[PDB]
Amino acid sequence: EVQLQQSGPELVKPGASLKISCKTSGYTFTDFTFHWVKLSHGPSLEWIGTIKPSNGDTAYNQKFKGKATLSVDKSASTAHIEFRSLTSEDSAVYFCARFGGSYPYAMDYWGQGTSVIVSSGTASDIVLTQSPATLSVTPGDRVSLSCRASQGIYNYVHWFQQKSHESPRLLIKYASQSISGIPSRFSGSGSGTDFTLSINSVESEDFGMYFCQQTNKWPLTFGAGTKLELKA
Amino acid sequence: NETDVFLLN
């Protein structure tokens, strides 16, 4: 059993530095690249950066270059992210994820997330357009979620489900490849710029947020999400 | 395919 275990909730003063951790179990730590993702309101997901644990090589989203430093402790099989000059804008849930599984790899295992509170006291990036932004349906309806890329990205699109108070869960990788344990009602299609996630019959347990992600170009990017909700 | 060397190899 593979697991990514993150350190507990944090609450800090503005201007502080903070190091949060992600400890692995059940596999060889140096196998797969680690990624850090910031969850903000919407919910919205942003990719911070990545570290290759075998040699410590990194790649960052330019937006977070002056803010976060990724590192690994190979002897402790633990990945770390260190923030500096923390402000109210950094209050968020931060997730660690590994980019692994059967080849070709994707963000298959995620940490449970770490809530970070910064207390007030007493241009060429691939754009992913998701539509419809909201789908209000009754269980048993058949739905299709769209993800349109700003330029051709071949089959480098992955789909995630994010339910309230939970970590993102990989549903489909590389536009159409199925994931072990994911129910057969979820399927994906598309290549180039138009990608579709289909849910053959919406179940009550499917309500939540759906995000698409591209991994063809740096920085890795997410769509703004489609909210799948119960029709009033 | 600029990310393949880092992510997949």
Image (cartoon, helix red, strand yellow):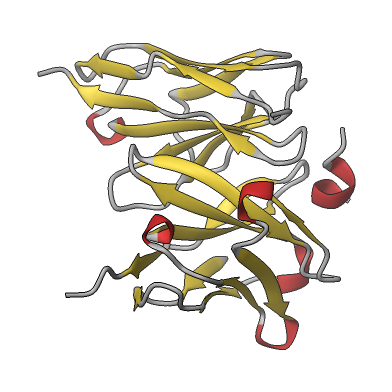
Q: Quadrant of the N terminus of chain A?
A: bottom right
* Of A115 and A89, the residue lying toward us: A89
User: Is residue A61 in view from this perspective?
Assistant: no
Q: Position of residue A90 (x, y in %)?
A: 43, 59
Q: Position of residue A114 (x, y in %)?
A: 41, 66
* Of A106 and A27, the residue lying toward us: A106
Please state if A203 lies on the left or on the right of A93 as rendered: left
Work out whether A178 lies above or below A165.
above
Q: Residue at x 22, y 20 (%)?
A: A139
Work out whether A47 lies above or below A116.
above
Q: Position of residue A136 (x, y in %)?
A: 23, 16
Residue at the outermost bottom position? A75
Please state if A226 lies on the left or on the right of A108 as rendered: left
Q: Residue at x 31, y 25 (%)?
A: A228
Work out whether A107 lies above or below A4.
above
* Of A208 and A198, the residue lying toward us: A208
Q: Position of residue A224 (x, y in %)?
A: 46, 29
Please state if B4 lies on the left or on the right of A184 as rendered: right
Work out whether A50 lies above or below A158.
below
Count of numbered marks: 0
Please state if A181 lies on the left or on the right of A36 as rendered: left
- Residue A122, image quadrant: bottom left
User: Is residue A52 in view from this perspective?
Assistant: yes
Q: Quadrant of the C terminus of chain A?
A: top left
Q: Residue at x 90, y 47 (%)?
A: B5
